[PDB]
Amino acid sequence: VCLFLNLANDPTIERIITPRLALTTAEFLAYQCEKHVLVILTDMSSYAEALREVSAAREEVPGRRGFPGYMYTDLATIYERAGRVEGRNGSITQIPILTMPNDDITHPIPDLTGYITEGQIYVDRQLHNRQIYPPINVLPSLSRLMKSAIGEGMTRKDHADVSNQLYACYAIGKDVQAMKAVVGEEALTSDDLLYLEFLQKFEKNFITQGPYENRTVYETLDIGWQLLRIFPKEMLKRIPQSTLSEFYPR
Amino acid sequence: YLSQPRLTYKTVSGVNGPLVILDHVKFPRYAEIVHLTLPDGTKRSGQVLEVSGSKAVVQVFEGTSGIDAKKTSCEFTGDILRTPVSEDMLGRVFNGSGKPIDRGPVVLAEDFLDIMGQPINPQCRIYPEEMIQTGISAIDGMNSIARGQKIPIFSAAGLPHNEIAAQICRQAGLVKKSKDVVDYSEENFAIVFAAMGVNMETARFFKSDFEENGSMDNVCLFLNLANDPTIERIITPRLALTTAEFLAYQCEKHVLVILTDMSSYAEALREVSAAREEVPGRRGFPGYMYTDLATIYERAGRVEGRNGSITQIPILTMPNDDITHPIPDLTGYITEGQIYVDRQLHNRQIYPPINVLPSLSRLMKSAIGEGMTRKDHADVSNQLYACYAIGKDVQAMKAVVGEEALTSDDLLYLEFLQKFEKNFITQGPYENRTVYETLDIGWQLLRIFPKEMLKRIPQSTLSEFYPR
Amino acid sequence: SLQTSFVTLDEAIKITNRRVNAIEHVIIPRIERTLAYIITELDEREREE
Amino acid sequence: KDRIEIFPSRMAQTIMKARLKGAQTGRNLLKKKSDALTLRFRQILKK
């Protein structure tokens, strides 16, 4: 483990170089010592703030929200220092984090971070308001490489359809909650009560883990199927019948 | 008049963006046209933007690229832009700059005029006194166009407003034939059409359609593809208006000018302003957009003592279907009346998708009347509108009240709705309906009910027209 | 038969009237105020630039 | 409570104007149903 601490009382300007040193060391450890490494950068909002400060000092022609127009270029220089190389063995797996001003997704910083990088996890506030931990909303979480990182041999033949179906059920359940807010139980039917029950048990069993709860992927698919069994096999559309003929009945 | 030899300079103190700054020019004047010759031999025109002592600035029309400092000639003309107007321009096709493009010859100018035009004295305005027919039954019957009225046509991206414009072009005219066709043969009507900010497919479509309709002998055409220089965008309208003026008030004709895609005009004007370093106004558009659109729209009407008129039908698109966007807002303020097209109606596969419910008019009361038309127009329009509004809101009612609780008269209202949308509005691209046919179809649609329900029609005309 | 239909239709009318009233006296003013605030904020942001 | 929680923006202006239009259409449609229901009530009590 190697560290680079920059407390809040330190000089502000040295933030623009701090991540660069870490990434340089990461490149060295990746392609000169052939070691697999994981990078973690924190509070990129402060990084953007430092860029704003240095820019406003120079009186440059500014951009949206006061930020320099060239933020995207700089963030591209910082994030694209990741990947693997032919003829080598090490790799860079980068996982930054950042805070959201006033929980606004359309704020420029998170927008550009979604645009450069490969999606989001979106620790959601409302789940945290209900003492849920990790309070993560699966619905906006995106992971482009997951589509081909799964399959027979890699993880299992039975990974993808579980995921897609569970996503669809979550989306429909939140839709049902919204429609209930509009009207209520009087115009709804049995299936809406089932979907709300599914949402409840999904926030009970799937998301909530605990500070040390270490799960395994096969057990995770088991839990996904236990949640999927709440409905009939017929109502499901995304999952082909092929997987249901092998793993639905129990 | 002018007899002095022209000057030319090999001075270039710098270039920046679409502008070229020089100096040591003798007695420069604003708005002076300037030619240029590059090292490679290309010729380009331009205009003077800034003047300050012996310093000058010229915005090159064709776009600045590869202009050396020392090897560049810059001839001066000493006159503002002047158009070679001429009656014989009908049957021709031009580009934005006025250079012909139909393999024809340069215009043998009959007279030279100022491109900007001059304001027309409000004292010598004449109120409109008679209607016209555009060939569209939905427009003539429900919403009259007088001689000299300024009616825009709001549309949006993705609608067939261009097809409507072409239809209006190939069928516009007069209805003086009420009394006799022998006196109707004296026709003195022409159309000038200014396609601007138009993509290539639509430009070709316009050229082909105008040539197909066989009435090109009274159509002037101006094209400005979106490739051409952005400044030529805001010079095409001035040429078109100057031509329309010269034809209207020097040939005593009846001209109908149709402008297309004023949003592209606004965008080009915005770009000119931003290049000119001026401070932005509201929404990024310049402050004096109101004055500019005013000086474009206000060139029309009628003149006392001259047998002629100018009618304007500008078109424009509303970004995001937003009715409070500045371009339609200012356009509505300056002009009189408005006509809509609605997404849903086009999405019902109804052509032309003309939504009459929010369509208004300002001079309909005085455009129509006994003599110039039949005596049975205004009441018919009121009845059609009232019946249609009843039918639509009644369909909204039956949507939840259930069709079983409906009265038989309710079914008559629904029948009126469906037949009105099936026949009156739908016409087809070539079904050239006249005003009289339109009123015939209107009476036929009204015949469904008894005269008792038709409570907007006077009994005096009921005893005459209803039992047909 | 008539009396049965009357007695049920009474509460039917009551619930419908409650729904329309709640809609017309709660949500519409709220949305309209939100739109006023939004227009103001957009104006502020443009003027700063 | 007095303001629907969202970040102001232009897109937000579009969505809120759409939601207002939806509420208005719902109100009109409910008014039509209430008209039919009171018609049934009156005709039942007619005689």
Image: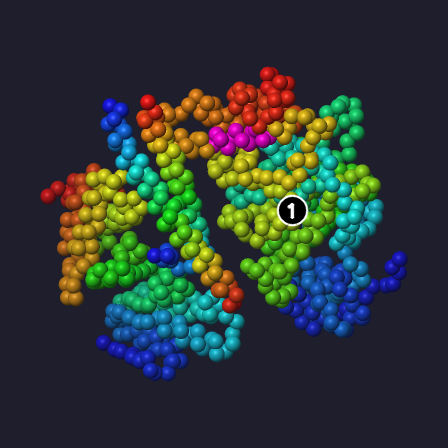
Instruction: Find out whether residue A160 is within the magenta segment.
Output: no
Amino acid type, mark 1: Thr
B159 w.r.t. A118: above or below: above
Q: Camera-side residue: B4 or B177?
A: B177
Per the image, the residue denoted by label 1 is B335
Quarter holding residue A30: bottom left
Q: Nearer the viewer, residue A242 or B350?
A: B350
Residue B74 location (% of width, % of height): 75, 65
**Residue at the extreme top:** B467
Where residue A228 appears, x then y in whole percent? 18, 46
Instruction: Tell me what residue is drawn at x 47 percent, y 58 percent.
Output: C39
At a point 71% along the width and 60% down the height, the residue shown is B46
Q: Position of residue A54 (x, y in %)?
A: 45, 77
The part of the chain drawn in magenta is B381-392
Q: Please name the residue shown 35% across and 32% down the image.
A: D38
Chain of the residue on which disc 1 is drawn: B
> Going 37% across and 83% down the picture, which residue do you hit?
A11
- Of residues A32 and B63, the one nearer the viewer is B63
Instruction: Residue at the far left: name it.
Output: A250
Q: Is residue B387 shown in magenta?
A: yes
Rendering colour mode: rainbow
Whether residue A1 sits left or right of residue B327 in the image: it is: left
Dividing the picture into quadrants, the one containing residue B195 is: top right
B465 or B101, which is in the foreground?
B465
Q: Is residue B314 visible?
A: yes
Whether residue B335 sits left or right of residue A118 in the image: it is right
Q: Quadrant of the N terminus of chain C?
A: top left
x and y, in percent, of residue B222 in the image: 69, 45
User: Measured along the vertical axis of the image, is residue B160 above or below residue B27?
Assistant: above
Disc tally is 1
Neighbours of disc 1 within 10 Å: few (<14), some (14-19), many (20+): many
